[PDB]
Amino acid sequence: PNPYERGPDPTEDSIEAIRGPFSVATERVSSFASGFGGGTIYYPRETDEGTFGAVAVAPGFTASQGSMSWYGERVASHGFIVFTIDTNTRLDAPGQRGRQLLAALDYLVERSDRKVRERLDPNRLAVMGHAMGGGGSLEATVMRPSLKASIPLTPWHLDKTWGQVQVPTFIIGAELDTIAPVSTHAKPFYESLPSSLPKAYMELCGATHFAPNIPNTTIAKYVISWLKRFVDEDTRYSQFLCPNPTDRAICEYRSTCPYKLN
Ligand SMILES: [Ca+2]
């Protein structure tokens, strides 16, 4: 059996639920932490199923952790440590945001309070971010190729080539976004990732740039499924990812399914 499985066998209803099966606690991290602007760690309270993987979550240009706060309880309650960070400055660029995502992960591994550290599997780490923070998610996977997953949400980056990334990457685009338009950001990034990388692209019908900053069940269910599949190696979640989702909220989906269990 896979020792990283947590929680009951999933259903489409259970991955859409606002509160997953774990209760959640928080730990605040001061902005004086090294290499990033501090943040909030959301973690599952229950320990008897084992330790958990972690995802560091970055905001976009001129945004702060509050724009990403809803991921904390939503995702942690399905069995993840979720660290919503602030950046060094509000004006930081995608490369800087990638470096800071890594600094936040290293803080979890090396410096976090014992309540977090005792719940963490330091070998199973992921990144996620919105807009320039999604560019940061891409960057972080080049800077740290041992990451288990990357989730660029309506990502923004001037560099359109990501052909050496080896970290499973799930890009979410917003159909009507004019700040990080999918035609020039999300889709080029997706198509530039290796054809043989486990990857997906989900475009949300009607959505605008700030769609990832408020609760969105279509985002949540597939973010949870991606993190389960890749951070936890949990093939009970393959059923939601492959074949491609058909939810009405989705206007286009691309993938490299099947994601062979490796
Ligand atoms: Ca700092």
Image (cartoon, rainbow, N blue to C red):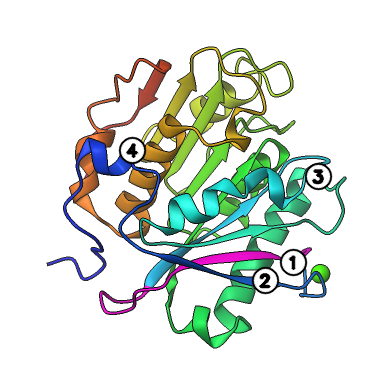
- The numbered dot on residue 28 is 2
The residue that label 3 is drawn on is 93
255 vs 92, left or right, is left
Q: Nearer the viewer, mark 2 or mark 1?
A: 2
Q: Looking at this view, is 125 or 215 the one in front? A: 215
Q: Quadrant of ligand 1?
A: bottom right
- The numbered dot on residue 16 is 4
Q: Is mark 1 within 8 Å of ligand 1?
A: yes
Image vertical order of residue 112 relative to residue 37, above or below: below
Category of crowding for the residue at label 3, using alpha-carbon neighbours closer than 10 angstroms: few (below 14), some (14–19), many (at least 20): some
Secondary structure type for disc 1: loop
Q: Verify whether residue 43 appears in magenta.
A: yes
Please tell me which residue is depicted at 36% across the width and 40% down the height of the picture: 198
The quarter in which the N terminus is drawn is: bottom left
Q: Indicate which disc, 2 or 1, sits on the residue closer to the N terminus.
A: 2
Separation of marks 2 and 1 at Cα, in angstroms:
8 Å
Separation of marks 2 and 4 at Cα, in angstroms:
27 Å
In the rendered picture of this protein, how many numbered marks are placed on residues? 4
124 vs 180, left or right, is left
The quarter in which the C terminus is drawn is: bottom left
The percent coordinates of residue 260 (x first, y second) are: 22, 44
Q: Looking at this view, is 194 or 97 the one in front? A: 97
The percent coordinates of residue 99 (x first, y second) are: 71, 59
Please tell me which residue is depicted at 63% across the width and 19% down the height of the picture: 208
- The numbered dot on residue 70 is none
The amino acid type of the residue labelled 4 equals Glu
